[PDB]
Image (tube, grey):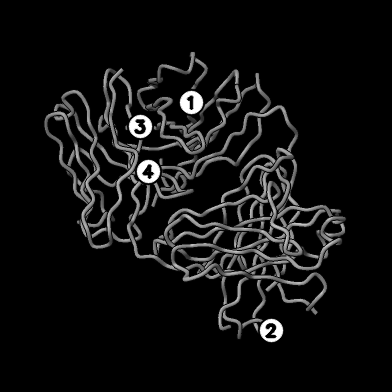
Amino acid sequence: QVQLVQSGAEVKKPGSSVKVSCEASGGTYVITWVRQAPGQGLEWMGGFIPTFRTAMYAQGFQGRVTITADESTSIAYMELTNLRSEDTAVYYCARGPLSRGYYDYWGQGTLVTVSSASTKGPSVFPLAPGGTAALGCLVKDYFPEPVTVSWNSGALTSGVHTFPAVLQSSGLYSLSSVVTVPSSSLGTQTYICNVNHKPSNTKVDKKAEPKS
Amino acid sequence: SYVLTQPPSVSVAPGKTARITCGGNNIGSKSVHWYQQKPGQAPVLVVYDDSDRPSGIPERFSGSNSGNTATLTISRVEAGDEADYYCQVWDSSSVVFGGGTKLTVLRTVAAPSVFIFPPSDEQLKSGTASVVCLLNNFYPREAKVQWKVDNALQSGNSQESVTEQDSKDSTYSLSSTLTLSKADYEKHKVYACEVTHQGLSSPVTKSFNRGEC
């Protein structure tokens, strides 16, 4: 029942530092940090054993990585200094049993975006609706990634397609989240998209209903 | 340092058996661990110490390691198995991962359901118009989407996005967005997206006239 919970998505200027936290919720082992650049593979950054106060780091980070822990609070930390645009990745913390070599518990990941640019929250617009109808929400002009989209506060999951973001000519992202529903439900049921953009602190709820 | 070699892709029909190889110089001398990563999710340990299996992992997942090749075998492949699979070892005080193998499920031709969405009134206020064409639940991934404005074929003003294989039916979905100024959008009436796909006898067009309800 232990769950590794990580800190939220961040934008960091190049030449700066990032500290990512990993909390062992209903728990307390080897703590590992693995990163993933978008569309690429898993890359080990290092491990740390708080009990033996021992750390092992990966070569290829120029000694910019520091892994720490606080046993009092059961939170693990990864600090990465001298951030460059190549460090834009999802950062995973993972826990494995002592001397075993594998990681049976993983955190949800933290997307760290290395950018000189300022954060921009999205504008959310509705995609208004035989037997099956389609509706959705357009999530336009945001930076950086990621955005999350739920339907009816998570009650509606079936028939949902949230598309990968496209990078527009503006250098900003845009995505659509769509859902197919029964035509008979339009006029009865209420469909709302819940959009969240953590880097900008934007939280928008938008109703996708047919025109007058 | 030590190199793990995985093929980038493996494709299998439902009910069939997938074999994901992990090549390494005398990999049989090491303990091989396997992770499954579904799109937008964290990796999940599926096989540890060559052939052992964690609690919630189906018996259909099995591992083997001898000589220069470790293999993850997935029997009776389902749409829920679509993911990227990574092998991992420890070598000279370092964690080494394979480059990953994407598992694609080979399903039948499925025609898309096509929907067109006009720009919202709220967006029009901002001086920009986004017209969206939706291709829902089709296979294979290749689809030609053509935008037509007052019968004039559009070019360089649309972008497409495609979902990963559906976890339940193995299809894809595509969104095509046509971006115009409020000026250009208001200068025309007929908005259409024409869809060419191998699951359709002839191309399907979905259209709307700027102004109707």
Instruction: Tell me what residue is drawn at x 67 percent, y 44 percent.
Output: A173
Judging from the image, what secondary structure is the residue with disc 3 in?
Answer: strand
Q: Earlier in the sequence, mark 1 or mark 2?
A: 1
Which of the two discs, 2 and 3, labels the residue nearer the N terminus? Answer: 3
Query: In front: mark 2 or mark 4?
Result: 2
Whole-Å distance between the Cαs marked 1 and 4? 18 Å
Q: Residue at x 66, y 61 (%)?
A: A194
Left/right of residue B198 with respect to residue A189 in the rendered view: left
Q: Amino acid at mark 4?
A: Tyr
Of the pair A12 and B85, the residue shown nearer to us: B85
Cβ–Cβ below 8 Å for labels 1 and 4?
A: no
Q: Quadrant of the C terminus of chain B?
A: bottom right
Q: Which residue is mark 1?
A: A68
Location of residue A119 in the rendering, given as x and y in whole percent from the top left corner: 73, 38
Callouts 3 and 4 on one subunit: yes
Q: Chain of mark 2?
A: A
Amino acid type at mark 3? Val
Which badge, 1 or 4, comes first in the chain's sequence?
A: 1
Element carrying mark 2: loop
The chain under label 3 reads A
Q: Amino acid at mark 2?
A: Gly
- In-front residue for pair B133/A19: B133
Identify the mark at residue A30; answer none if there is no mark: 3
Chain of the residue displaying label 1:
A
The location of residue B53, given as percent across then percent down, is: 22, 48
